[PDB]
Length: 56
Image (cartoon, rainbow, N blue to C red; front, side, top):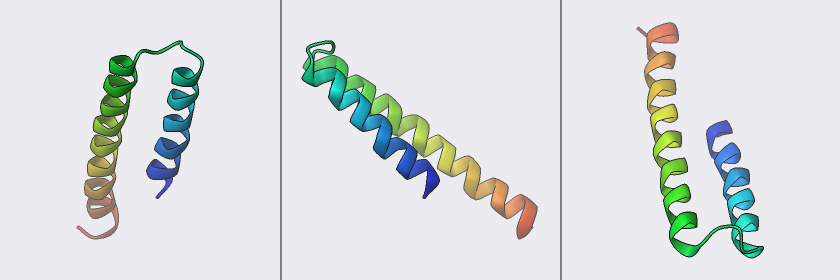
């Protein structure tokens, strides 16, 4: 949930950056994809760490 909310705000930042002509469409796209890839990795690691520590 945390990792989602985090993402959900970072997205907004990126969106802002696109509103004011700092990012092109492609750049925004790439940054969103990168963000979601990293987030996905984080939730994977969180799943496995939760298993390892609490339910081995």
